[PDB]
Length: 201
Length: 201
Length: 201
Ligand SMILES: CC(C)(COP(=O)(O)OP(=O)(O)OC[C@H]1O[C@@H](n2cnc3c(N)ncnc32)[C@H](O)[C@@H]1OP(=O)(O)O)[C@@H](O)C(=O)NCCC(=O)NCCS
Ligand SMILES: CC(C)(COP(=O)(O)OP(=O)(O)OC[C@H]1O[C@@H](n2cnc3c(N)ncnc32)[C@H](O)[C@@H]1OP(=O)(O)O)[C@@H](O)C(=O)NCCC(=O)NCCS
Ligand SMILES: CC(C)(COP(=O)(O)OP(=O)(O)OC[C@H]1O[C@@H](n2cnc3c(N)ncnc32)[C@H](O)[C@@H]1OP(=O)(O)O)[C@@H](O)C(=O)NCCC(=O)NCCS
Ligand SMILES: O=[N+]([O-])c1ccc(O[C@@H]2O[C@H](CO)[C@H](O)[C@H](O)[C@H]2O)cc1
Ligand SMILES: O=[N+]([O-])c1ccc(O[C@@H]2O[C@H](CO)[C@H](O)[C@H](O)[C@H]2O)cc1
Ligand SMILES: O=[N+]([O-])c1ccc(O[C@@H]2O[C@H](CO)[C@H](O)[C@H](O)[C@H]2O)cc1
Picture 1 (cartoon, rainbow over the protein chains, first blue to last red):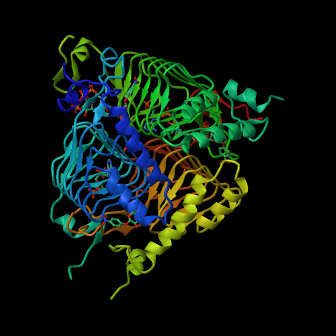
Picture 2 (cartoon, each protein chain N blue to C red):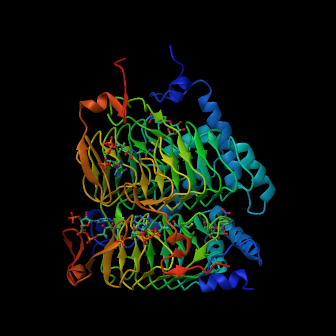
Picture 3 (cartoon, helix red, strand yellow):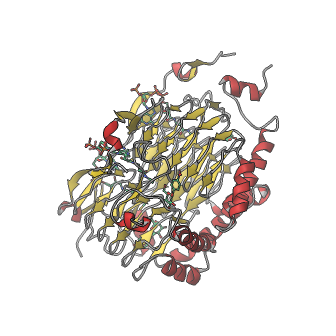
């Protein structure tokens, strides 16, 4: 009728116990395990590992272990990427991160959800909607980005926010659920934290 | 007068550095360590490890390591249980999980609390009130379930909510503190996510 | 002109890929790794490990692994300190915890933040502001403490609150963002949980 991997790209409900899906997760979870168990001095091994576990990684990437994901091969990353401890990405489908992105500790990305009505999820049915993170975005600690959410370039997501809707570019959004609190103006070019200014030359 | 293990069941303040409580945690914490450090392929080992660490597990159970708990012998799970990375269960007392429950990444269940007045908790004193999760319950990412809470059947707990009170069955609840936002009606039988419908068969 | 480490203490923007900073992070991430991968029965090793990785530790301390930090040597802890699973402390600068402090599972402390304007953080520039936690402080699960924050003695930070502002002593604070909800009175000396009193004798 309609293979399982096609329902995924169509945004329809599906299950993932076939078509080599399980085998893919294994290869992935395997690489992830090597990475999470590598010694802090195994810098080279860690470097090539990330290049192999993610679908696409730009130059100057650095991920602080542990890192958790479903396949890993559905995650595409740009340049100068940086993620602190416990980054979790549920990538049953595509996850794209722009350039110069910064992710604080314990952040969680999920393109997958489950039908709310217990009827549609009897067999653990799920749906997947890609997540797009712009360039020069900065995610706070303990943030949670839900399915099909887009974060516009240059935005900032406060610590602890639950993002369930796209966030426009050039704004500071935060809250549960996440909401735009204000746009990044030129004052932000002088004041970097509370009452701290930054002199020009 | 009244032994420590009896205060626990009576919901009174207690400490746990005696009566074998320490020993119990050591056995539990040992199996947990073997589980968490287990290679992705060690599927059979993993399957028996969970059977030996939880007081009760039903058929078709799956727990994505790492998992964290205090004893593991105070956790009782039904059938077709599924939990993602970093589930954490502080089980100084009973925690009962129903049938076909789904647990997203980084969730924390805790039956233990500390008295608010620093006086009463001079020695780390604590109290424990059992948590009960109904059947077909779906818990979002980064949720926190507090002592004595009861989640009714078929309910959904949005991502990031702090549940501090009983959640009735058949509702979608969320927020900090978690509040019921709506009852699950028949429209949810048709619309699974946002504007996505699902044709009959 | 003005060395990177001096800007840190001055609270100016800085980057840390020099002046042995990276090297320092390695020694720390090394001890940290030994700690997190240590077997539950390695009680003595665990104990000398926490003495060696933190700047200062008071007697009767206990940290349930895993534990995550940046350097570890900028962290100062008092007496009878207890931390549950997954405590994250980003310590690019001083972090001070007082006496009899209780931290629940999955808490994140960070003295570092990034300038909101993508121009100032083109190179991942950062700023660090020391965190100070009073005596007899109990932090609930999944809380996040942002830079420069100060929590007064005897206070309780409810589960899931994001602390962006100083919390006065003797208060129950909670919320996103954390807000004072009430003062700890004398009723808190009789009632410990909901409707549970404690017979003085
Ligand atoms: C977003 C952030 C950078 C600053 O936002 P800002 O506009 O410059 O700061 P403000 O104080 O002016 O914020 C305005 C209001 O939003 C609130 N607020 C701040 N951060 C918030 C957050 N994460 N969630 C919800 N509300 C938040 C403030 O309490 C303030 O309250 P008020 O309106 O009653 O006065 C900071 O709040 C933050 O959370 N940073 C993430 C830090 C982190 O996770 N670091 C980890 C190491 S990289
Ligand atoms: C709860 C959920 C399933 C959908 O709830 P729903 O009723 O079908 O969705 P709605 O958009 O109609 O929600 C209504 C409002 O609540 C808000 N809301 C949604 N999720 C929320 C959450 N987790 N916390 C707080 N508020 C939330 C919405 O932003 C919306 O705002 P509005 O009233 O201003 O329009 C979804 O929000 C969610 O969080 N799912 C968890 C996903 C997850 O953790 N997946 C991990 C992989 S299994
Ligand atoms: C803070 C705490 C100790 C109790 O606060 P309290 O004043 O004694 O309790 P109350 O029920 O009177 O709280 C008053 C209100 O705040 C709300 N509230 C409680 N905890 C909250 C939290 N963490 N965040 C936001 N709101 C919260 C309550 O729902 C209540 O609602 P109402 O005004 O509509 O009635 C408890 O809520 C808590 O979260 N403890 C942390 C537990 C934990 O993380 N344990 C891990 C193992 S150590
Ligand atoms: O409970 N079930 O029956 C059930 C069985 C398999 C499931 O698949 C799993 O879901 C995870 C998110 O929650 C990830 O998407 C993971 O990659 C996927 O295999 C989800 C639920
Ligand atoms: O800080 N103390 O003195 C102190 C000493 C021992 C404590 O016991 C511990 O608490 C944990 C939750 O926070 C779990 O309940 C764990 O099983 C219990 O042994 C809690 C606090
Ligand atoms: O993205 N960058 O270019 C970049 C490079 C190095 C950075 O340093 C790191 O930041 C962490 C918090 O997010 C901790 O402060 C850590 O100790 C620090 O070395 C932060 C960002």
